[PDB]
Image 1 (cartoon, rainbow, N blue to C red):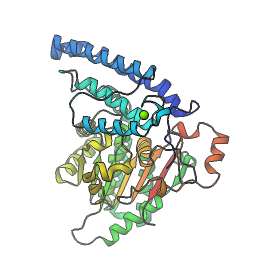
Image 2 (image 1 turned 180 degrees about the horizontal axis):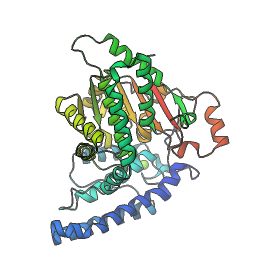
Image 3 (image 1 turned 90 degrees about the vertical axis):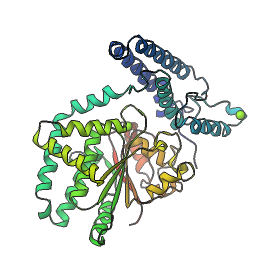
Image 4 (image 1 turned 180 degrees about the vertical axis):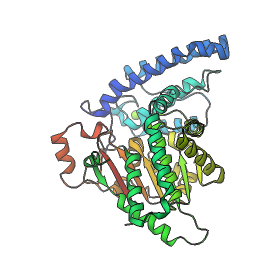
Length: 415
Ligand SMILES: [Mg+2]
Ligand SMILES: [Mg+2]
């Protein structure tokens, strides 16, 4: 397996992200805490203000460690994954030879660096009762929802129009509607040129055959490993409703993040809050969607799962050893959809793979069930391309894979 992406290459996007973007995220977190000082006093009294100041102090220390490339330190505050994290940090140090020194922001794998930063943010918060419940990214995730109301209404209206007629659609029209919603989940004719890899036909073949072959009382389970909250989450819920309504799935299982993560990533609180806001909307079609979605969850047609593994630094190839219960759960899927760039990085180890490497190889043994990554590119990693394809893009458009402009549907599994 190739070397990890990291800040060792000062010309790398990982370097640029660690040097400039991560400090910016921490500053904004600190700003968010500062702006909530009055709310914390109203709800918690003086102990809330002392806790806000403590959290800010800790986050300021964290930002200084990053800005000065200090070595990583063990996590201290008791938490469900503290010991697993410290074991992983010990393991990561063991990979370093004498010349490499100690794990640190601009030397260690970029995946570990970013995951460590968010876990240290969470440590600062859980060290600061009574504000230890606070989600420093909640305001931004709520803002994405409120800012997207027109597109959310339009998409909920589209889905409900679709569902009204869904039993009159032939197989090929149903397929076309499936492909449309998959592209909405990714991001339509104007955007098609920016789909670099399109395995959507293999998803249709897989689920269509499951539907045609399904025996009585048998299940077709589709798992969705989520990325961002807000409009992205809505596109995934809309897809999942279509999957049930079209009978391409009989159950949909969702996996989010146990803690606030990578700013926007959906936690159980974001998931429940968004569905509540859609359900209690006064718009006819948004409200009907939200009601239907809460009913799917009640019946077990939709299931939300929390698992700590997704907010660990480990590459997904480690899941069988580190989270065998989760791996066995994923093996019950008929299809797993992984959303977004971080999932892609974890699927491929965040390594400097050649463009030509097959996705199957880059997964490094992680083959729980048929799976597809639905991803816009925000990292210097992309495998499974045709010879010369990524090279031509680099030469024509040096930023191509880091701007979120290009997308993929990249599949591993049968057919
Ligand atoms: Mg050493
Ligand atoms: Mg995200």
